[PDB]
Length: 195
Length: 196
Image 1 (tube, each protein chain N blue to C red):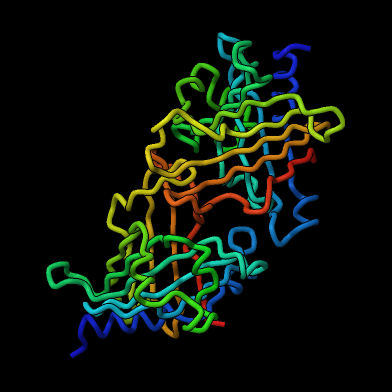
Image 2 (cartoon, rainbow over the protein chains, first blue to last red):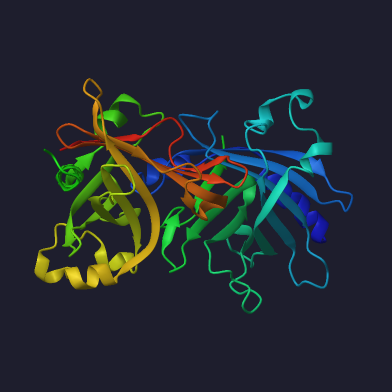
């Protein structure tokens, strides 16, 4: 097991169809039932896999409220992490709506997916969890950045936990210039489990 | 002989009070949730502006508002060619003002600190009197191009506000990315707030 083995498990864990329905019925005050549908979209020459990931309210699965292109690749050996997960905005999101259930001929091809990658939103450095912990891999967006690199604008924070049987715990939060949470769940991560 | 200040006080009175989208959510649960809106006068300014505190909460968690605003309702300046000007502002420390409208005036931030705790100017809407036979009393949008916003990958935000009779409020807040994909807010239409 090296970092590309880890990345392949992380990449497989992130794809598929998932629901937060167990968490939604457990705690309806704080969590909704969200459907996550993820599929591989392109392979980089470096070996990095580009996955399409989208999230929708369970009652409107063809109207996703979040659409992303994820890049999962093994961490460089000089970087002290196992797997790197990066999410990107999509230049036009509507050509990509429900990308996972449309045949390859009538959806963006691997040729175009590299060009449709928009602004970089998150980078998460995952590490193998300790012995006995429930997770397989866990990590967050870096608590710190380069000095004077924050432009004073909105910033998002993302925590990611990969568990057994392709269970994904995702906590995407957004903040304003005065550090007040504005979007994303307040209590904790959404727990996505295979249908 | 009804002035612009008259229309602003009409708009102000219809914005205050406790409101819910529960009929719209019961009608269309696929696309709309039951959201509680509680608004009350926050401060009255010397130029004649009315400052309202307005929060929005998921009906299951009314004590955890997901959106807290300070709304300024005033008549449009004479050069602008509109009836009422409504502008929304972020709040300095949102948790300071958490559920501000049920706390009595002694134990909530005073009008002086309220205008002092005003944050970044988010939206500005120019409402106009609707014609007879229309369902609104006042309606307006953010002028094209919207206003800057940075949430979820957005680059700007739009807001549509319609004041209906008997303090019914239609509010549509949306965020769009740089390439004009909607990135937050409802996609199908405005939230319909009816008084409790």
